[PDB]
Length: 63
Image (cartoon, rainbow, N blue to C red; front, side, top):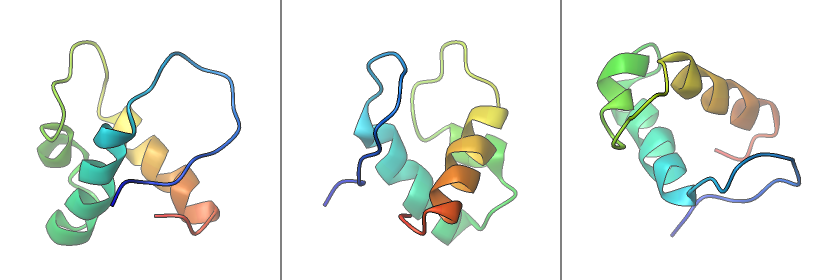
């Protein structure tokens, strides 16, 4: 299955990156923003992008 959604404003983001992020943090354990970041083909995103999407998802208990 894929990750949930959330009404917001931003470029066309791929839910795939989320699937790997959620499971990645669950298996690799939070804190490994870098190790987990390797999940998707990063081009210009920093580790913050990982800890961010994770933090937000945590608040909405969606992850």
